[PDB]
Image (cartoon, coloured by chain):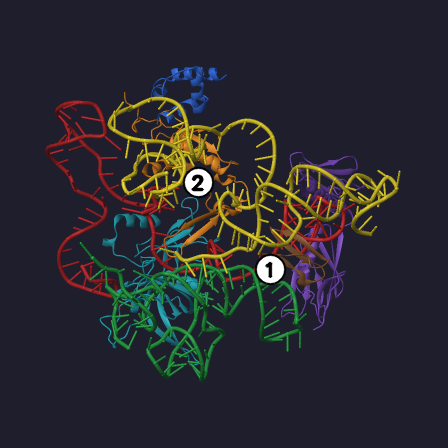
Chain colours: A orange, B brown, C cyan, D blue, E purple, F yellow, G green, H red
RNA sequence: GUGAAGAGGGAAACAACCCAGACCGCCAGCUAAGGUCCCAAAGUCAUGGUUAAGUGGGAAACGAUGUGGGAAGGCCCAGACAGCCGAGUCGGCCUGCGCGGAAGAU
RNA sequence: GAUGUCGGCUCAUCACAUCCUGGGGCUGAAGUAGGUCCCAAGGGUAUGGCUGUUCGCCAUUUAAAGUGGUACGCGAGCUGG
RNA sequence: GCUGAAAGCAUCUAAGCACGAAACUUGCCCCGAGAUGAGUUCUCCCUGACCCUUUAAGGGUCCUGAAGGAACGUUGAAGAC
């Protein structure tokens, strides 16, 4: 006998909705990455995507511990000589709240075409409303 | 202000205090006694 | 505030009674006709769109003609847009003339500059020429060195080199308004503005 | 691969992989990981019965 | 600790309202409100207020002392009130009051105008003297410090704006 | 002792360090060093303590009411320390973990 | 079985142990003008006589004429003292 | 600097509140939806019959050819092409 392998043409996926108000950033990101990759199903296969769709609400109310709210720095370089730039957690929350969760989850997925594909199933919002009622998501408690 | 690595009381009116993680000496009699660790 | 679209006619001078000569640029400003109003509910911002001039019928395609016929105005040679401030209102089909600048003191003018084509570093970036004698060998207007050694081992982004020069959008700020003539549709400003004779200009009240 | 699938199946019935293996050893069940993963994918009632056996052994 | 273990008396003519950690004190001179820290519990026995730590915190006693001092100041303020005095020293230095604005001449090439906040009153019994009245200790202190910052007492002659009861040292060249 | 003339696993990458000596095949099982939140196989295990510096994840002489433990002292209900009346207060010793001293070139 | 080595010209980029401009504490700080330490790298930062010189001395200017790294930056870019 | 305990006093800090620089983020000028996360708004154009088969985002025959575009010519204060 040969071991079972899943097929991209016949996999099944489902829609969940989550609330981030007051949760710890990293300990929520781990769960998001787990369920986007599909490690919780018995059909898991490293070279196929067998994950689920997840909506996240209230991204501007996520929490951190310690003195991180004023001391965690995000960096990036623009490609021009001398172009190194930075921002703090508070600043990032003020201008681009969704990026905070997006960057953290993107760091915990596999690197390559399949990982970039897995990232496309995540939908992050800043308030308490979404426009995906036609898909009928179910509430997930994390 | 005196910025140094060894800071200590120089007369009976000196006082030691800790502010925002720094160790400082303040005096109510002599402005020359004002010290900061660094 | 809103501004207007006009055309560059030429340059002349004005003599004053104290014996001063003011050099001026002459701008022709016909009536600007409103074609579309954009609001927050339907578009997401607040602006007006205008046309000016005239255009021959057999050069107007059906999409353009339908757009003009919705507003109920005659066809012109282009379409431009201006952003609105709080407490400014307009209606479709309305006409705006050069009497808008009756009490303004300074303006900003925008246009497209003359094109020089492919240019060297001496003319494009004001480099210095090397020696014309004393044994120079084929290197008189050339750029020189362009980097360092094995560290870093490349050329940095944004280096100054030879290439296309001119024929781009330019703005010049804070020009005195010298005269406003409404019976002949003329505006006279002090100094030079970008472009060539016969080109299009955008005129606005000064931001600083 | 077999180990990953068995962990996923066991957590859906309420136990972790390490505990499940310990309970099977204490109950003297000698089915290997290839067959365990095959049953996990193709027959879920039987897998539930195996999990109950392990839990009883640990109790 | 010791400061927090002394209860605060509530005299006749003052109303005390408690809701969670928000407290309101209302008297003849006005009304004051304050929110307290999450490690203090406050009780209104019969005519006294008492303060205590809440089990689960490691700095309850310090917070209790702070809360006691603050409530004591509020009770004094709503009945009597607080006052402060400022004095000017120099040649050509002058103050005046109009509405809720103090006009100051202090040797500059322009005048100084200071706009009082809501709840603070000022008076000038003499051209070289200012008196402030109010019901909020911190606000009145801040206003006095702001007024002093315009021209600080200098060490060779003593010129500028000073507090009434302040000792200003001087030295020789 | 190992490399030279030695492959496999660990130390991110890394002849000479740690574990261990490859005759051939297998879609069986147990362990070594090193590990068990996600990249990435396995405890978001159990019970009692310490740290608030992202210390952990670079460094000295020396400086300071950070704060956990221990063995002894001086004064005090016959009223102590502080300030202007009623329960504690002073300064040395040994020891665990943190803090300053700490400036570089795409 | 080859990695062209001093000085000049052209063209640069980074650090901060800061020369100028910006903000402060102490002074044996009356004022003008100075001394010393802390914070700060946005922009700016000479022409000539002599000598192959880098340096250096001299003449006359400037708010000021910073200190270092980049194969003691730069010859498939130039010179050849 | 204000108010304020731990530490009955004092103390800019532990809980609270206020000032403060050419450095930081904006305000000024130019590019910018290949932003594959490929966005929005206004206007215009196309309204016929059959056959086969392995029956499907299937192949073919007759009738039809719009909005618009490209090509060629006379050329520009646009340009190496």
Residue sitting at x 22%, y 72%: C137
- Quote the CA–CA distance across marks 1 and 2: 42 Å
Q: Chain of mark 1?
A: B
Viewer-nearest residue: A92 or B33: B33
Q: D17 above or below C52?
A: above
Residue under numbered circle 2: A104
Viewer-nearest residue: A78 or F57: F57
Q: Quadrant of the C terminus of chain E?
A: bottom right
Give the secondary structure at mark 1: strand
Q: Quadrant of the N terminus of chain E?
A: top right
Viewer-nearest residue: E15 or C111: E15
Residue under numbered circle 1: B3
Residue sitting at x 30%, y 57%: C77
Q: A141 above or below C14?
A: above
Picture quadrant where residue D36 is located: top left
Q: What percent of the width, then of the height, locates residue F73?
A: 77, 42
Q: Chain of mark 2?
A: A
Viewer-nearest residue: C21 or E66: E66
Residue sitting at x 62%, y 61%: B2
Give the secondary structure at mark 2: helix
Q: What percent of the width, then of the height, locates residue C132?
A: 25, 76
């Amino acid at each position: 006998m040969k071991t079972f392998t899943a097929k991209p043409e016949t996999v099944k996926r489902d829609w969940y909705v989550v609330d981030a108000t007051g949760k710890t950033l990293g300990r929520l990101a781990t769960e998001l990455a787990r369920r986007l990759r599909g490690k919780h199903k018995a059909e898991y296969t490293p070279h196929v995507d067998t994950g689920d769709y997840i909506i996240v609400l209230n991204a501007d109310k996520v929490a951190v511990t310690g003195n991180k709210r004023t001391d965690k720095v995000y960096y990036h370089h623009t490609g021009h000589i001398g172009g190194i730039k930075q921002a703090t957690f508070e600043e990032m929350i003020a201008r681009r709240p969704e990026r905070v969760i997006e960057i953290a989850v993107k760091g915990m997925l596999p690197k390559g075409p399949l990982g970039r594909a897995m990232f496309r199933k995540l939908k992050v919002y800043a308030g308490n409303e979404h426009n995906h009622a036609a898909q009928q998501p179910q509430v997930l408690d994390i | 202000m005196k910025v140094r690595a060894s800071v200590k009381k120089l007369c009976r009116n000196c006082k030691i205090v800790k502010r925002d993680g720094v160790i400082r000496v303040i005096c109510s009699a002599e402005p020359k006694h004002k010290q900061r660790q660094g | 505030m809103i501004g207007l679209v006009g055309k560059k006619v030429g340059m002349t001078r004005i003599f004053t009674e104290d014996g001063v000569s003011i050099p001026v640029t002459v701008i022709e400003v016909e009536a600007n006709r409103v074609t579309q109003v954009k609001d927050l509910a339907n578009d997401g911002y607040r602006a007006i769109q205008v046309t000016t001039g005239a255009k021959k019928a057999n050069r107007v395609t059906k999409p353009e003609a339908g757009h003009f016929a919705k507003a109920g105005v005659e066809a012109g040679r282009g379409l431009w847009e201006f952003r609105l401030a709080e407490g400014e209102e307009f209606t479709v089909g309305q006409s705006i003339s050069v009497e808008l600048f009756a009490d303004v003191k300074k303006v900003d003018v925008t246009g497209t500059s003359k094109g020089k084509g492919f240019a060297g570093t001496v003319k494009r970036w004001n480099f210095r020429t090397q020696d014309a004698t004393h044994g120079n060998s084929l290197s008189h207007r050339v750029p020189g060195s362009i980097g360092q050694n094995q560290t870093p081992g490349k050329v940095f982004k944004g280096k100054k080199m030879a290439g296309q020069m001119g024929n781009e959008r330019v703005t010049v700020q804070s020009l005195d308004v010298v005269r406003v003539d409404a019976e002949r549709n003329l505006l006279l400003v002090k100094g030079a503005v970008p472009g060539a004779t016969g080109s299009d200009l955008i005129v606005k009240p000064a931001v600083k | 691969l077999w180990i990953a699938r068995i962990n996923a199946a066991a957590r859906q019935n309420g136990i972790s992989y390490s505990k499940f293996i310990n309970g099977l050893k204490k109950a003297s069940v000698e089915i290997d990981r290839k067959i365990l993963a095959d049953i996990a994918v193709f027959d879920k009632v039987a897998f539930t019965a195996l999990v109950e056996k392990a839990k009883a052994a640990l109790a | 600790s010791r400061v927090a273990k002394a209860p605060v008396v509530v005299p006749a003519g003052v109303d005390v309202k408690i809701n969670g950690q928000v407290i309101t004190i209302k008297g003849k001179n006005g009304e004051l409100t304050r929110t307290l820290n999450d490690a203090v519990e406050v009780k209104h026995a019969d005519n006294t207020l008492t303060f205590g730590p809440r089990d689960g915190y490691a700095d309850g006693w310090a917070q209790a002392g702070t809360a006691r001092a603050l409530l004591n100041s509020m009770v004094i303020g709503v009945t009597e009130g607080f006052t402060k005095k400022l004095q000017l020293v120099g040649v050509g230095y002058r103050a005046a009051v109009k509405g809720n604005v103090i006009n100051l001449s202090l040797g500059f090439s322009h005048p100084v105008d200071h706009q009082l906040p809501a709840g603070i009153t000022a008076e000038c019994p003499t051209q070289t003297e200012i008196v402030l009245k109010g019901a909020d200790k911190q606000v009145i202190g801040q206003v006095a410090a702001d007024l002093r910052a315009y021209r600080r007492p200098e060490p060779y002659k003593g010129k500028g704006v000073r507090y009434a009861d302040e000792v200003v040292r001087t030295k020789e060249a």
